[PDB]
Image: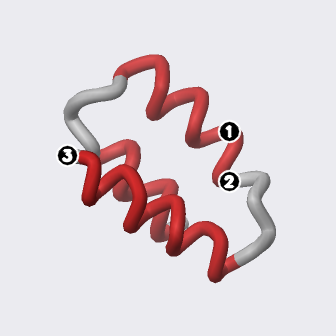
Amino acid sequence: SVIRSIIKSSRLEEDRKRYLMTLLDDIKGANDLAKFHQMLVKII
């Protein structure tokens, strides 16, 4: 939910936050999620 919320709150990727939502929501790894979060949030 944490990462799911941030990407959904990421006002840049429309369909990509939607797509990445159904992806990350399925990501059952807390550490890997955090890395994906650090990833895109450092991208922007």
Q: Quadrant of residue 11?
A: top left
Residue topped by disc 2: 25
Between disc 3 and disc 2, the foreground one is 3
Q: Is residue 43 above or below residue 11?
A: below
First in residue order: circle 1 vs circle 3: 1
Residue type at mark 2 is Asp
Between disc 1 and disc 3, the foreground one is 3
Q: Nearer the viewer, residue 9 or 43?
A: 43
x, y percent for residue 33: 60, 67
The residue sitting at 68% across, 54% down in the picture is: 25
Q: Which numbered tag is attached to residue 44? A: 3
The residue sitting at 38% across, 43% down in the picture is: 8
Residue type at mark 1 is Thr
Report the Cα–Cα distance between label 1 and label 3.
21 Å
For numbered disc 3, what is the local secondary structure? loop
The residue sitting at 65% across, 71% down in the picture is: 32
What residue occupies the far bottom of the structure in this picture? 31
First in residue order: circle 3 vs circle 2: 2
Q: Quadrant of residue 31?
A: bottom right
Q: Which numbered tag is attached to residue 22? A: 1
The residue sitting at 26% across, 58% down in the picture is: 42
Query: Within 10 angstroms of label 2, few (less than 14), some, or many (20 or more) residues?
Result: some
